[PDB]
Image (cartoon, rainbow over the protein chains, first blue to last red):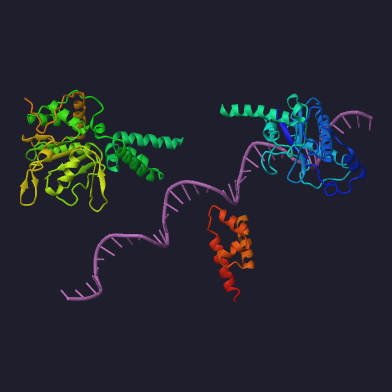
Length: 478
Length: 67
DNA sequence: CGCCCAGCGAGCGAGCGAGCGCCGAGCCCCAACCGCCGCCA
């Protein structure tokens, strides 16, 4: 059952708000006095006297007129006498039984017209909005606000003594909290319990946010760190994304986020190792290259798997020795292009050799030549150990343990020093590499090793693991 | 023209009050009244109209009146 | 003669705005530094 919040501002100053009021009315209002009921505990000195009687008479006549014009004396109501910022007011409530919303205005106007020339004896109050109904929206166009039973304990009972003087009603549940703070607090707590029970009954959650999350996830799962691979893999998705104006910065943001997440939490074997199994590995190019040079395919695959996973520790490098165009550069470039963030050693630049090798996954050393000026840092980078370097036109940076591959025709152990050579640093470099004598030359129609071939080779390697002995010279197949 | 708007009448009244009191720089604004400078600065645009009004009042007081 | 249209009105709420606010990208001007030149045995 809804209720209408009728606001009635009770005049405070009878001389300023009700000029010309009869003396008998003021005398009767000042002579009347109330008393705390038997079951009461509120201070009577704080509560006023004449305003209380005025509000009582007002609400009584209002309720009688409502019951007479509605033809329904059996109806629920609720009155509460309070004190505004600088004027007394009330918060009367009447049920909607027999009085619709479209007729509330006419009944209120009739009650207003009946009030004057009867209670005030012709005199009218000066306080604006002395008898109206609370509307929904703030304005003349706002409709009637039909509150509920839960509106009393939510915007009336929580008040205190200075904001609550006397309240009249007929409901049994509210009849006890008419003039008592203990019952008021009890009912307020009992209602707040239910309010909390009903209320009970970071990550951004939105369609665009979830879509972007899934997009960046699926892009990182495929291995697209830049726009180069985005168009190569799926050129339609890039077009669909770039069509939106808001996607311009989002594309770069996703690329940077993927790159950072890979540089922080990702390993090379994850992308190097294929997902689906392989049933025919003999057709692979790496398998043929390894079988033509006499090397055991299974042993070479296990060595590569152990080197990619840093299983050997110090021996975390592979060196393909042999003439040019013998299956070294092909496999090296294939393994370097398969994984994102591949490095490149510039042996020609002795000042900044390990420049393009920071934040990489596969350090490629094409035609390397060890020298006395790059032997110390090389011994640390090849052995899988943290060490700082000096970049070209950039600040220094550390190179975490990352797999390294070398492919050259000259002797890497031989340390060159101008017009001479020394083999002092022979054992340190020999105990940290995997020499692969690839002396057999391939045919002109062999073709380059694609990216899927490396994945299939690594997958077949993971499926067939064998004991790999820590040695410099790899054992050739029988 | 002319154009009437609730957002322009306040600006015109502010310009008139500034020309009447004679606010030269922004320091005198706080001296004459702090609540006004706080309210006009609390807007979303912040300092998009304060400098404009200051320059307008200065130019008006310069071209019209003199020392 | 106690109803008659029936003529009147007073809102009356579900609409209509329109006007502002607060982002949202999107240009725009400005300052701490790079390239190239002057300066002497």
